[PDB]
Length: 419
Ligand SMILES: O=c1ccn([C@@H]2O[C@H](COP(=O)(O)OP(=O)(O)O)[C@@H](O)[C@H]2O)c(=O)[nH]1
Image 1 (cartoon, rainbow, N blue to C red):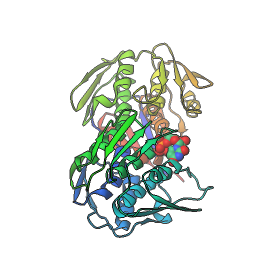
Image 2 (cartoon, rainbow, N blue to C red; image 1 turned 30 degrees about the horizontal axis):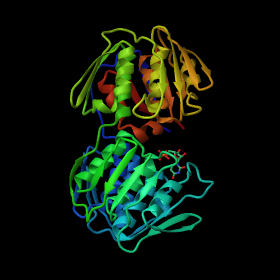
Image 3 (cartoon, helix red, strand yellow; image 1 turned 90 degrees about the vertical axis):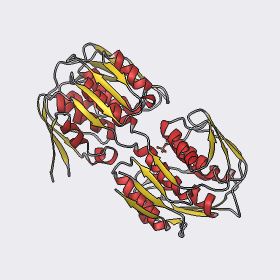
Image 4 (tube, helix red, strand yellow; image 1 turned 180 degrees about the vertical axis):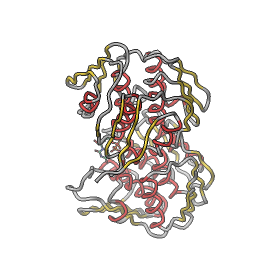
C-alpha cells in the first residue's frame, strides 16, 4: 500500500506543467467513437481511467495507441457492447452508449448491480437518449439503446443538472436529424471542452458553458487533432502549494479563464498573481497567507473541488476564516486529520471555522478524498518533521505523478511501501 513520506518544512517554489484534465479527456475519448477519420487527442494525462477507457475502446473495435497523445481510429467499430468486466471500475463507461447508438444504431452497456461499490443511477443518460428517438431496452444489469437510421433532434429539459448526462445528450445529438436543445445543461469548463472537440470534428454546437446548449445535427464527424484543456483543479492545487509556503510558482500549460473564482480568492489571501494566455504565476513574497472567507457554489463560482486546498490555506494563514459548502454535505471529514497536525478549527454544520497557526507538525494521516488527500500531502510539505500520508492511490487516480511535480518544486517527498 503506497504512502507518501514527506519531510518538512520546505518552501514550494519554481515551475510546474499542468496535465490535461482527466474530466475533459474522458468524455472526449468516448466522443471519438463518432469520428469516421483518425483522431489525435493531445495533452491526455497518464491515469488509471484513461487506460480503462483505451481498453474499452479497443474492445469495441477501435484502433487505439498512446504515448503525450492518445491516437484514435474508430473508422471501424465492430462490437457495440461494453461488458461488465471492462466497465466495473469506471462509471464513465456509460459514455460509450450514446456514440454507439448515434453512429451505429445500437449500443449496450453493462451496469453494476445495485449493491456494488460506487454504483449510481444513469437514468438521465438513458432517458436523454430516449428523447432523441432511441429505443430503450432494460433488464437488471444492463441498458441497450437502438435506432433505425438517425436519432431525432429533440427539445430536452433537464430536471436535474448533470455533467454526465449533458455529455451523453450533446454527443449523440451531433449525429441526429434536426436541432436538439438542452435546457439546464451542466456549465463546467469540461463540458465546453467536449463541445469544442465535437465542433472541431465538424459538429454544430453553441451555448456550451451556458444553461442552454443547442446542437444542429450533421451528416458525420471527421478526424483531426485536438488538445484537451488543462486541469483546473490541479492548477488550483499548485497555486495553493506556493500560496501556503511563502513561495512563488509559475504554472505552465494553464487556462486562466477556467479559474476566475479561485484566482480572485487567492488575491484576497494576499497573493500576487499574474496571468498570460497559457500561464499563471503566484508570488507570496515570502509572506504568510491572509485568512479568507470562502463559499463554494456551482460553476463559475468558487469550486467545491478546491475546498480542501483552501481549508488548508486558512489553517496556516494569519487570522480567522470560514469556509462554507453551500450545496454539498459532509465535505470536512479530513479536517480532524489536519487538527492532528496542529491545526486549529471547528466544524459547524456545512462550515469549517479556521484559526490559522504558524506551523503544522508531522503526523501519520489519511483521507479517501482525492482533494483532501492531496491537501494532506501539501500540509506534509510545510509541516515540521515527518508526515506519512496513507493510501495515496486516491491521488494517483486524479493527479499525474504529483510527487515528481512536488519534488521539482523543492519538496522532500517520496513514495514508500507498507503492509
Ligand atoms: O444518470 C444520472 C446522472 C446524474 N444524476 C444526479 O445528478 C448529480 C450530478 O451528476 P453528474 O453527472 O454531474 O456527476 P457524476 O454523477 O458524474 O458524479 C448526481 O450526483 C446525481 O445525484 C442522476 O440522478 N442520474
